[PDB]
Image (cartoon, grey):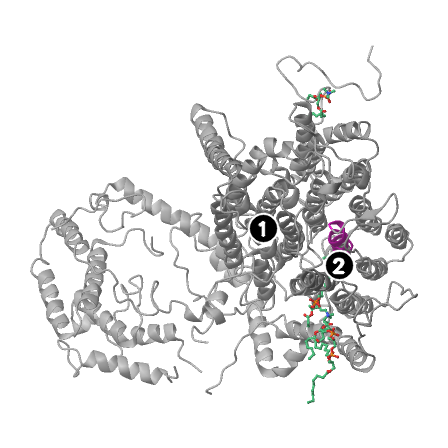
């Protein structure tokens, strides 16, 4: 007798859009975070060596991060 | 013991001390009765368009649509350029504009003359 | 004694619910509504937004910023180790100038 | 159907021989639709 | 500006003056005992010239009473926390979700609450069954072309519900 | 850039020979793929611009606006159903192909090497918008709105062509580098003053400034959502883009002759922010908001500081996103209740519990919330104009106060306090509208994390 | 706030604070009795009665209603309507 029916408008569409939003962001949020972490913990960034004598680098091998 | 309560355009005259409410004509009684009749007929039509279980959309208040089309589109007719309208138009449209234009001319001429002399505080004034 | 019209009494307000309770945003086809929701939340977020965030999160040094950092470090080390003041003014050499006379 | 369409009186303005009637252009009757003047 | 009549009454105007002055004297006068003294003084001041047989002298004393009241009112009167201007005044208007809604739910949430939705279905059938003939006949039978009042008649003919009851019965609980 | 021109062409017969109830999915999917491929452009580095031909080339001013165009296409192509979903298949395909052709001329216009080509694709952008707003305007003065749009934008924009032909045959070609690397000062004669007034006044019409701004609000309140959002965002920011490019010539006389336009822009910015505080017709508030912010953009362009140009392009991109989104929420409320007014559709905190977050977040991105891009743009414009004069910052902050006032009044008017309890037709919020809101907001916050993209040439 | 209320409580409390008043008597005081008609107190004191119920239960009732209560049964009914006294 103490409890009564309380009225709240239609939380189902709220919850459905929120669940779909988080799932279809995190479907390739976590694999890309795992990918970038495994890159910069198992491949190296680079070192800062000078240009050797009689040698040319390309337009890559000027950049720190390996995915860059 | 009373300061007579002078009104203003912001301090509204309250419904108690009018004092025109206390000497009453019969035509004012007729007017109040017919005004009650108008509000009663409007509430009757509204409540009959309000409690239909078949009705779905909005109630289509004609006074709101009438006020909106009175306020937006029906300003331009009617209009004639009067001496009052032309005077107030050239006052509110051009006056303050030419005032701020005069003060910007004054400030810029002072500043450029002062830096032509060079006695500003631009010892380092880098992010211009 | 006139009407001036003959068309339908219009409209009927199209409640997009009450025939698909599981419906997404648009009209009452059951399959292609699901395909629209799936394609906008996959090929609009899962491959566009997050991969765009990783792409423009890091890329080559945009408008030559970190190169400018490292080149300025080297040049300030040089110009402090060789006596002359760093950022000498008159960036064009006054040997290579010819003023009009008076 | 909630989209406005031009009514009869919106196309009544596209009538007569001229578009803007004045104090001198009222007698411009519209032309016969057959392009045949009656004898 | 009242639903049933056009003008209040003379007596109704004096009576509203008495309630407003007594309430402002409550707000002016704390400790409640000097309040009770001053309230009985006010009641005596109304009693001293209550039995005057004129009418223009009655409206004379009423008008000067409003003058000598509006002189001596109180700036922030103690209005209750449900009145307009009060402390709450639809505090809980956050939660008055109306009951034309709650039918736009998904059927799984309707499968969570079986009995309340079944009884709402029978109330809605009671609304739809007894709408047209009874209510519209009682509303288009007794009035004149001008209604001239806002009191609407009860249903006393034979049977069913009074006219125009739905959005007066099914209002929220005011403390949800 | 041809790799962006030609799939925009190829996306057009897609819409024709896709079958019934399958044109939608194919066009949305493929335009989003075009958006990823567009985001692959961002290569621009340091010293020069990048040249995608003697015909196409990209400054770093044109890159975020181009990505904005190819990002605002699929958002719009999803945004424009439920008010033409009941119409015919042929008219539906014609509308979608018209939006694709408008995208094509916008890409033509943003990667315009030559100013003659820029003018031709400028009014080529002008062409389909009249057809869109007139055929689907859904009100009775859409004829008046489209006609004022047409004759204002032409009759301002037209002697610009004569000035560009004169520059074409007095200084050789009109590549932006050879218009640059050669540009000589033009002294205080009168013919130079009229050439300046022709070019700058054509773009003054396009922005608009205050004396020419009634061009805009009819073309927004009497137009569908697609024409409204493309019109506001891409056409006004394209006008600003064009003024940014053409102001490299005429260097000395802008100090002599550019005072009254600054004046009309400032005082009309104040008067426009004041007029959008008291109006009804919810759609029109965002229109006059756009007039106020582009008057701020005009002050920023006509003063000639690198801080001013960075703040100008940041304000352009942020306000394009914010005003397009806020148009879309206004259309969502209009699809809920067939009103267009403001004092009618009250309540909506109790009902529709999630829509409050999008209203609040869009109103705060219009409020100049401080990590957002809008405040970055407005802040650098305020810094540059206080460098211009020590006294004009009063008008900037008064614009700031009134802008916060009307934006937050627009929030707490429609969606705060009491449902009118005679509405009883509004349905809970679809997934489509909230998908559109998430496609608007999330790029703006992710640019608020890293705004080194959207700052323009003078980074 | 957690008060419980019922019709019994409001009936007994209204009849209580009408019983405590001076110039009527608890001898002939039913639930169903008018004020002017059979108890015989004046309308001025009837508005003092209404002031007492307002000052007790803690909420104003308007004078558009306070014309026409006149009997404790309708007083109990009206305040039970305003507070919505059911579970
Ligand atoms: C005790 C035992 C536990 C100790 C744990 C310590 C950490 C160990 C570890 O992971 O070391 C490997 C490694 C150590 O770094 P490092 O090798 O010294 O330097 C690598 C780079 O120079 C620097 O990294 P980067 O250049 O690859 O990118 C940095 C950037 C990366 O941010 C981005 O690239 C932005 C976009 C990321 C993906 C977002 C996807 C969508 C959202 C998904 C989630 C919702 O920002 C961050 O990672 C945030 C600061 C924290 C740095 C690490 C601490 O950690 C990482 O690289 C962490 C990557 C995290 C990615 C983001 C995750 C959250 C979102
Ligand atoms: C504009 C036109 C429409 C564009 C539509 C798509 C926009 C996509 C914008 C994504 C922006 C992502 C920025 C970002 O995450 O930067 C990394 C941001 C800021 O980092 P940053 O970009 O300053 O530099 C990081 C550089 N490295 C990776 C080498 C260390 O990182 C974080 O916020 C950490 C989590
Ligand atoms: C507004 C009209 C803009 C017309 C194009 C701009 C222009 O050159 O106007 C100057 C033209 C005339 O100037 P002009 O273009 O003949 O310039 C001659 C320049 N000198 C003297 C060096 C040879 O004036 C107008 O168009 C008047 C309007």
Q: Are marks 1 and 2 on the same chain?
A: no
Secondary structure beneath label 2: loop
Residue tagged 1: B126
User: Outermost residue toward the bottom?
Assistant: A1
F404 relative position to F327: left or right: left
Would you say the beta carbon of the disc 2 residue lies within 8 angstroms of ligand 2? no
Residue F57 picture location, percent across and down? 83, 47
F370 horizontally vs A26: left or right: left
Q: What residue span does the magenta drawing correspond to?
A: F61-72
| Residue E40 makes an appearance in the image | yes
Residue G30 can be seen in this image: no
Q: Main secondary structure of the magenta part?
A: helix
Residue linked to disc 2: C64
- Whether residue B71 is in magenta: the answer is no
| Helix, strand or loop at mark 1 | loop
Chain at tag 2: C
User: Looking at the rendering, which quadrant does residue G36 occupy?
Assistant: bottom left
**Could you tell whether E68 is left or right of A26 in the image?**
left
């Amino acid at each position: 007798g103490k409890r009564l029916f309380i009225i709240k408008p239609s939380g189902f569409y709220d919850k459905r859009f929120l669940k779909l939003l988080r799932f279809y962001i995190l479907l390739t949020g976590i694999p890309v975070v795992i990918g970038i972490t495994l890159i910069n913990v198992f491949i190296g960034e680079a070192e800062l060596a000078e240009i050797p004598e009689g040698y040319v680098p390309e337009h890559w091998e000027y950049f720190k991060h390996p995915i860059s | 013991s009373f300061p007579k309560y002078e009104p203003s355009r912001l301090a509204s005259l309250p419904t108690t001390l009018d004092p025109a409410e206390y000497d009453i004509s019969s035509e004012t009684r007729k007017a109040q009765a017919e005004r009650l009749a108008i509000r009663s007929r409007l509430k009757r039509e509204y409540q009959l368009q309000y409690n239909d279980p078949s009705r779905r959309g909005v109630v289509e208040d004609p006074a709101l649509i009438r006020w909106t089309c009175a306020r937006s589109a029906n300003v331009y007719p009617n209009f004639r350029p009067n001496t009052k309208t032309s005077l107030l138009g050239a006052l509110f449209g051009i006056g303050p504009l030419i005032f701020w234009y005069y003060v910007f001319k004054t400030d810029r001429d002072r500043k450029e003359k002062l830096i032509q002399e060079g006695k500003l505080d631009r010892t380092f004034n880098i992010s211009y | 004694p006139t009407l001036r019209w003959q068309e339908d009494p219009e409209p009927e307000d199209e409640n997009l619910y009450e025939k698909n309770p599981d419906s997404h945003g648009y009209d009452k086809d059951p399959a292609v509504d699901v395909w629209n929701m799936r394609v906008v939340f996959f090929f609009g977020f899962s491959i566009v937004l997050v991969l765009g965030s990783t792409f423009v999160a890091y890329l080559p040094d945009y408008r030559m910023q970190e190169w400018a950092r490292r080149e300025a470090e080297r040049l300030v080390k040089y110009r402090e180790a060789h006596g002359l003041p760093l950022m000498e003014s008159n960036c064009f050499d006054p040997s290579k100038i010819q003023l009009p006379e008076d | 159907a909630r989209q406005w369409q031009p009514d009869v009186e919106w196309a009544e303005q596209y009538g007569g021989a001229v578009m803007y009637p004045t104090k001198e252009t009222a007698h411009w009757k519209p032309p016969p639709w057959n392009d045949v003047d009656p004898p | 500006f009242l639903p049933s009549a056009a003008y209040l009454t003379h007596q109704q105007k004096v009576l509203q003056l008495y309630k407003r002055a007594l309430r402002h004297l409550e707000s002016r006068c704390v400790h409640r005992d000097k309040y009770r003294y001053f309230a009985c003084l006010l009641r005596a001041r109304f009693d001293e010239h209550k039995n005057e047989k004129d009418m223009v002298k009655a409206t004379q004393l009423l008008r000067e009473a409003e003058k000598e009241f509006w002189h001596g009112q109180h700036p922030q009167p103690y209005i209750f926390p449900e009145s307009p201007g009060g402390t709450s005044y639809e505090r809980y208007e956050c939660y008055k979700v109306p009951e034309w809604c709650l039918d736009d739910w998904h059927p799984s949430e309707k499968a969570m609450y079986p009995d309340y939705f079944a009884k709402r279905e029978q109330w809605k059938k009671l609304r739809r069954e007894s709408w047209e003939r009874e209510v519209k006949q009682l509303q288009e039978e007794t009035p004149v072309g001008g209604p001239r009042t806002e009191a609407l008649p009860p249903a006393r003919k034979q049977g069913d519900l009074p006219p125009l009851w739905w959005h007066i019965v099914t209002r929220p609980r005011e403390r949800p | 850039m041809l790799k962006y021109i030609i799939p925009t062409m190829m996306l057009m017969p897609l819409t024709w020979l896709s079958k019934n109830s399958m044109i939608w999915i194919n066009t949305t999917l493929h335009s989003l793929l075009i958006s990823l491929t567009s985001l692959l452009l961002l290569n621009q580095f340091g010293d020069n611009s990048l040249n995608f031909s003697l015909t196409f080339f990209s400054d770093s001013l044109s890159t975020p606006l181009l990505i904005l165009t190819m990002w605002l296409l699929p958002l719009m192509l999803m945004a424009s159903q439920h008010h033409l979903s009941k119409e015919n298949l042929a008219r539906k395909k014609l509308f979608i192909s018209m939006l694709i052709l408008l995208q094509l001329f916008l890409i033509m216009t943003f990667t315009a090497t030559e100013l003659i080509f820029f003018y031709i694709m400028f009014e080529a952008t002008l062409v389909p918008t009249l057809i869109i707003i007139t055929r689907w305007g859904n009100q009775t003065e859409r004829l008046n709105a489209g006609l004022y749009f047409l004759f204002y934008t032409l009759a301002g924009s037209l002697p610009l062509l004569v000035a560009l032909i004169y520059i074409q045959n007095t200084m050789g070609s009109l590549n932006f580098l050879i218009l640059q690397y050669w540009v000589q000062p033009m002294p205080n004669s009168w013919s130079n003053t009229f050439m300046w007034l022709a070019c700058m006044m054509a773009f003054m019409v396009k922005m608009p400034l205050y004396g020419l701004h009634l061009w805009l609000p009819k073309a927004h309140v009497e137009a569908p959502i697609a024409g409204s959002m493309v019109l506001a965002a891409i056409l006004l920011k394209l006008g600003g883009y064009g003024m940014m490019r053409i102001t490299l010539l005429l260097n000395p006389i802008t100090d002599f002759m550019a005072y009254p336009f600054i004046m009309l822009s400032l005082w009309g910015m104040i008067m426009t922010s004041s007029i959008c505080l008291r109006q009804t017709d919810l759609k029109s508030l965002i229109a006059y908001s756009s007039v106020s912010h582009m008057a701020l953009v005009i002050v920023a362009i006509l003063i000639q500081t690198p801080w001013s140009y960075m703040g100008a392009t940041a304000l352009m991109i942020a306000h394009g996103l914010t005003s397009s989104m806020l148009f879309c929420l206004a259309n969502s409320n209009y699809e809920r209740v067939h009103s267009r007014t403001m004092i009618l559709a009250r309540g909506l905190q109790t009902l529709l519990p999630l829509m409050a977050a999008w209203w609040l977040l869009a109103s705060l991105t219009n409020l100049a919330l401080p990590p957002s891009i809008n405040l970055i743009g407005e802040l650098f414009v305020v810094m540059s104009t206080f460098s211009w004069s020590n006294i004009t910052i009063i008008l900037m902050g008064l614009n700031m106060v009134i802008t916060a006032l009307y934006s937050l009044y627009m929030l707490i008017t429609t969606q705060r306090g009491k449902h009118t309890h005679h509405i009883n037709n509004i349905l809970p919020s679809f997934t489509r509208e909230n998908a559109l809101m998430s496609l608007h907001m999330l790029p703006l916050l992710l640019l608020s994390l890293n705004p080194k993209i959207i700052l323009g040439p003078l980074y | 706030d957690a008060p419980p209320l019922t019709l019994e409580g409001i009936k007994d409390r209204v009849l209580y604070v009408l019983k405590l008043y001076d110039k009527i008597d608890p001898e002939k005081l039913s639930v169903n009795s008018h004020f002017m008609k059979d108890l015989g107190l004046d309308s001025l004191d009837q508005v003092e009665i209404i002031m007492a119920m307002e000052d007790e239960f803690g909420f104003e009732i308007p004078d558009i209603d306070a014309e026409k209560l006149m009997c404790p049964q309708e007083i109990v009914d009206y305040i039970a309507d305003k507070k919505d006294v059911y579970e």
